[PDB]
Length: 112
Image 1: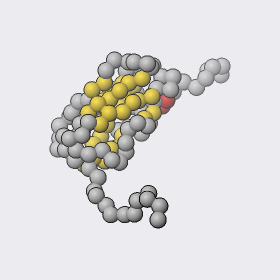
Image 2: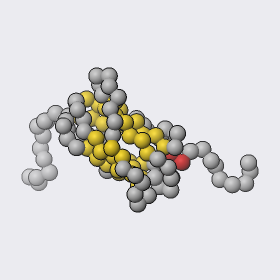
Image 3: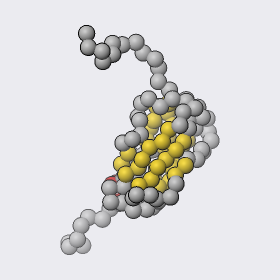
């Protein structure tokens, strides 16, 4: 296979930005967009509760060459987002998301 490009996995092209690593609270609607960057397939989203129950997410059909995920953290802690692509785990998943920020005291942006 000298000629041609390197074929490993298109899932590696999948990325996530909208998602907020830190800031998501409990009982709050958390949704983001999963960019393919050329990839074309199906995106399966599934969150794992810290208790021991496999929860499900909401991912409508492919639109504008992109997918939208929607799920609410029934409990606190760092959930595990299972993101797969045409039978291929994306680089970085499961995406660890911290649910529940601790109100900390510290100077703000207000210039002094």
